[PDB]
Image 1 (cartoon, rainbow over the protein chains, first blue to last red):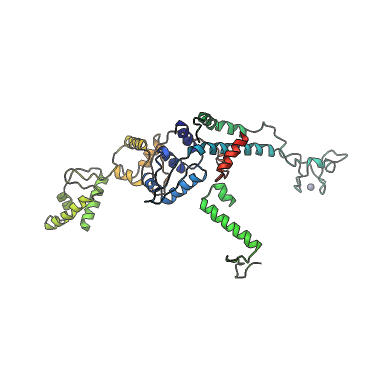
Image 2 (cartoon, rainbow over the protein chains, first blue to last red):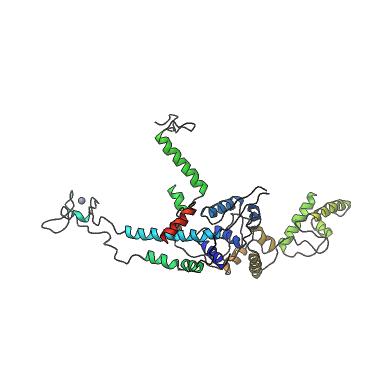
Length: 184
Length: 48
Length: 165
Ligand SMILES: [Zn+2]
């Protein structure tokens, strides 16, 4: 290993449970600590430790194969996958938030106070008075209501920039990744 | 199931919940499944 | 032999006093309202059998220092935790009360110092630690929007990154 994976997992704990964070830190030794040896050292309940290890295994962080022999859980910390897993997690996340941004720009735009029946901007001809100028609802000629939200007045959002900034430590740590090792 | 996934509930909780969801859907499609329990109407009468 | 376990409980309360000093059996037997005759000799045979397995430490000379972990201060807690996290991790609910002031002022002395006390284990367990490096404060919406299954898509992650590349 190298400082890459050390700092990486150290900052990766920040997402999952801090109870999982202590267990991840126990990978300080790559010695592949066994489940019962972990009960001796981590001492978390066998059920709590089992749940925690399984949750840490599911996201492809670590891999375990207790053989048979007392049985010895083949604990691990698969670092080669770790980097790709974190990259895909942010890769999907950056996509989901940008799509949420763009998909939030569409709305009916109009309403009637009574009858609460949004129409569309396209209904202007039906929802209008040749004379009075105020847009009036079809089955209640008493509408005045314009837009509950006018439009994306602000820039894209503070949400996207907030993700950009709160993750600048993660971006910088993946810049420290910088492919230190060309191995498998 | 949606709330469990939202909260990040236990994997076994989600697994059993998905099992029950599958059972309910398959039972609604067909209540005469081979070697599986029958969904009653709280009165002993199997649902149609 | 039951009176012997009672003597063990007595010396446990003696630890609780914090005035633990090198002692012997006669003074304890007197203060616990029991005599000194051949009965003390047979119970001392049992007591030496105890000295063969005295997890509650009962040594022959200067002794009775039960707690496998035993120091007494806020600095003591800090430094023991420090060396143990150099060893890597540790701490249980019984350690503090066996080692130090009576089960109060300890969660207090932990929360007061720079140590943000670690009570993460089960309701009856406190794995003490002091955390220095920052758990990256992540918005809960970001903390759990991060939840996209990706539970067994290994080759899929390879190819997906190769695609976005
Ligand atoms: Zn109306």
